[PDB]
Length: 106
Image (cartoon, rainbow, N blue to C red; front, side):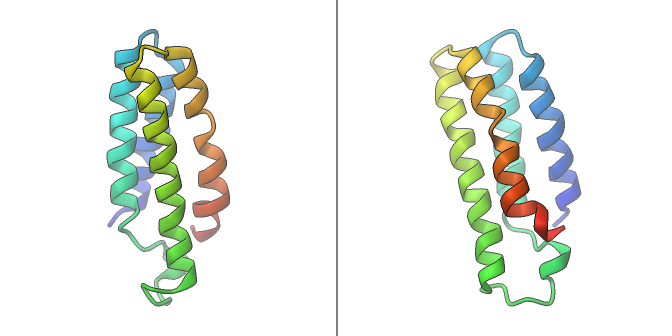
């Protein structure tokens, strides 16, 4: 795969969400983030290429994305209910998960 590509998608869409004025814009951005996270979850970060695909590190790498997808889904539920501000707040917490789970592997 190509993590930097999905990584770009996640960053630009966080910006879209931050600047959004309506729920539909937030929903569309979250959709792109979910797709990007799903792709990234199947890739192997550079620091784990020599590791086993079933290694604790790879499982940690993949679980971080399960958590991310989970948070994205939580934000999507909010956006789908018309709660723009709450969904935007929810999206601000994604960086916390990314830095602690995935960042150490790049």
